[PDB]
Length: 125
Length: 125
Ligand code: HEC
Ligand code: HEC
Ligand SMILES: O=C1O[C@H]([C@@H](O)CO)C(O)=C1O
Ligand SMILES: O=C1O[C@H]([C@@H](O)CO)C(O)=C1O
Image 1 (cartoon, rainbow over the protein chains, first blue to last red):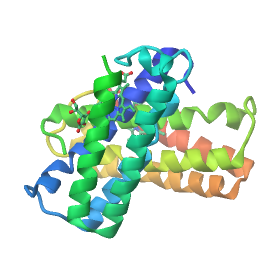
Image 2 (image 1 turned 90 degrees about the vertical axis):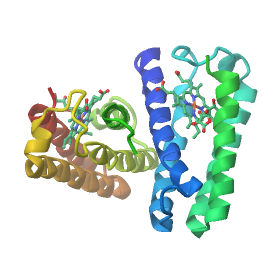
Image 3 (image 1 turned 45 degrees about the vertical axis):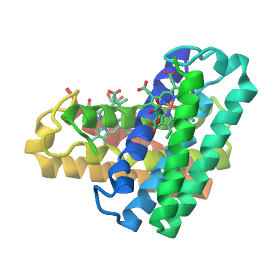
């Protein structure tokens, strides 16, 4: 859906921006500094779930650019693993939110954050 | 969820970028230049539906900036109307996609585009 490589870059960057907002906005809730409304979190994690599936199709052949390291394409299996671990952690987070269970939410949120960071470290410039 | 006004601006801009991709990518399909896969479109409009609900909360009090005209806040009812018409057209588009009906899809897509443009003209700089 990306006329030029740059269009894929702008796409993925915007997806990550939104992912970051939907993830990061729950930190004061996971930390206890903002109140916990299970339905609010259930709805928010649904948004985050949708968003979290979006970037991957925007790392197609020939879409090198932005802060994407070239190893994303030369180590495609390793990047596929980091991405699939991440989305798998998203499934666990949806399950926790869907349960309305704050401890399971805190643990799932921590795992998701870790997978964000793991890819950050390997595959962002 | 926006520490500073600028954070709301970056949020909404990213939502619109993604909306634009998910809307605009269907043009060759609505035009007949790319093939029509009803399930592909059903899934895509589900994404667009999620995305299309996102910008509005990022035009909160005190988030003036970007290409947002100040009339968005001084004419809050008029902007609320343009936004609600738009999202209502999104519901019609979801119904068409969910039906797998290409003519209803083409008409719904046209109405959505028009609502995009109507707000563009009034409320973007
Ligand atoms: C888990 C929820 C997250 C969060 C919160 C973020 N990421 Fe990543 N990200 C990845 C790559 C390759 C990039 C560079 C993209 C490019 O420039 O082409 C990024 C970028 C970001 C950003 C910055 C976006 C921008 O405005 O430019 C942010 C805020 C961000 N990410 C947050 C790669 C990955 C992963 C690879 C498997 C995973 C997993 C994540 N990111 C997860 C997250
Ligand atoms: C219908 C599906 C659409 C599409 C495809 C787009 N819009 Fe709008 N949009 C609105 C406002 C006030 C802005 C300015 C935001 C800001 O800068 O603070 C925008 C911006 C855009 C963009 C540019 C995003 C960027 O990268 O900076 C794009 C690509 C875009 N829009 C497309 C306002 C509205 C509406 C008010 C009710 C409605 C409806 C729409 N936009 C709808 C759409
Ligand atoms: O929670 C997160 O951890 C990483 C980053 O902080 C690692 O440096 C990231 O992208 C997040 O949003
Ligand atoms: O389909 C669209 O119409 C408007 C714009 O072209 C009006 O100038 C817009 O934002 C779209 O994505």
